[PDB]
Length: 330
Ligand SMILES: NC1=NCc2ccccc21
Image 1 (tube, protein in one colour):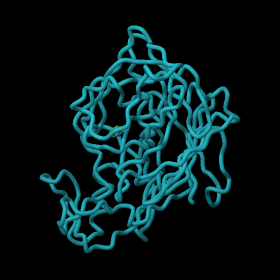
Image 2: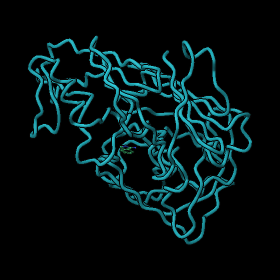
Image 3: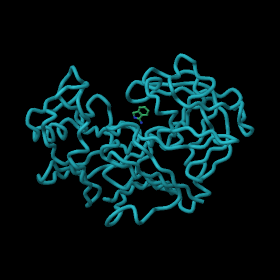
Image 4: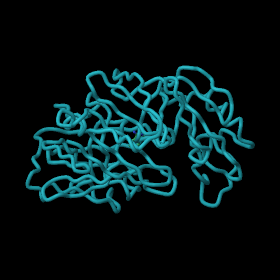
């Protein structure tokens, strides 16, 4: 089997991407944030504290003839930005772009933090990291991909995120028309539950490539590119007036600037992030200070190849017995 679904930016800055997902019988379509940096499929629901729902579409398990309470199971998750959610668990039928999994754990939110409430466009998350990170207790549950894997034509999914435009998540096949040149594959460590890999270095603009190992995660659920302070300083030093602002919480730059590209290595291959991809617009409405899309990972404890990096590539998440990642230009 295979599946293919379009993923769409939630706003004009590509702050996140949403993908429609069918849950239950008859189908209830919710727009979920596909997140290769976590492993829970959770949704706003009829159980979510009413004051914490503001415009989201909810899953109502009592209206699904295939929903079953997973007795005794609860979940609770925190994310890198300090947001969180928790609740109980149903199993139900879940379909993505024509690919169906029966008995998928659908984690129903009883509580969500303010950032989730305030984002009316995201109805929940669909985790695509390794199932070892799934938070369901006392019986850990499998991700949609793990449940689907054995049925797929090939045990893979691909992320093809757009810059200020829709893109695609495919399951079970590689669309050879969706990228240019070849796909370069690179080793993955699953020790921390992430799609963790080692970039071979970087360049800033038309500058020379610096060969250096950068260990990080491919994380579609993180907006920006978080890299070591040395690398980030080298980037922003090429932008007149750019500076790190403690009050704003990262590097900012004059909105009048033209940003240089940023290149990252994948083995001997190179992925080029155009400068425009690194512009996240005014820090507040009407400001001439703009927020940078490349930020320091110092204090996070891990480097993160988030959407800023991934949307410059066609990315293969290869879930074979020994997982690997693939990157192609597009
Ligand atoms: N994977 C994620 N990085 C940041 C974040 C916030 C909210 C949900 C998921 C994520």
